[PDB]
Length: 209
Ligand SMILES: Nc1ncnc2c1ncn2[C@@H]1O[C@H](COP(=O)(O)OP(=O)(O)NP(=O)(O)O)[C@@H](O)[C@H]1O
Ligand SMILES: [Mn+2]
Ligand SMILES: [Mn+2]
Image (cartoon, helix red, strand yellow):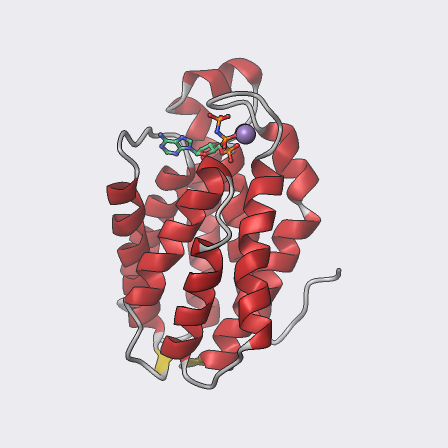
């Protein structure tokens, strides 16, 4: 059980999320067909997440709000590609939501996923569905619903991942090129990789490098 997430647990979630995305960067690159099939979503997201991870690793804190400012700054100064910019905006909104907190419970975690979705949609001038935005939105809606009756952040994150994966598997039904080529959205897949790392960290586990 995880009732509260402090700054070091959040840092662990960042580090293991980044490692899991790094492990899967070639896989995510291989799916990248939209907007242009230039095969770089995984690399772009990996480089972005790595910039946030390095800032965090060099400036740890027990205070989740302070650690979030560090992570957010690292992403925003290292964003690469459409996918990396969107990832940085998703977590800018997440981190802004907890800026004054030292630790957060499952309800505030869910509210922070939702705040990130709102920030990222506002940052994209013409949002398209079937994308990283769709997956993030469906994950956040799942988070809000589950957290209402679920104190344990491990159980919450497991549910978020189940529902995020259902949304990811549905992305070809929203975006024609995905169904025509036969792939799920690369940006959403990269985000799922980060969320899977989040769960490993909540369990006190490490992603194999
Ligand atoms: N308008 C959009 N709305 C939502 N998500 C988007 C949009 N445009 C791109 N994406 C996401 O960004 C991913 C592609 O990211 P990425 O490969 O990093 O883009 P890019 O290579 O930088 N730009 P491009 O060369 O124009 O395709 C997609 O799989 C979607 O998840
Ligand atoms: Mn590109
Ligand atoms: Mn690309």
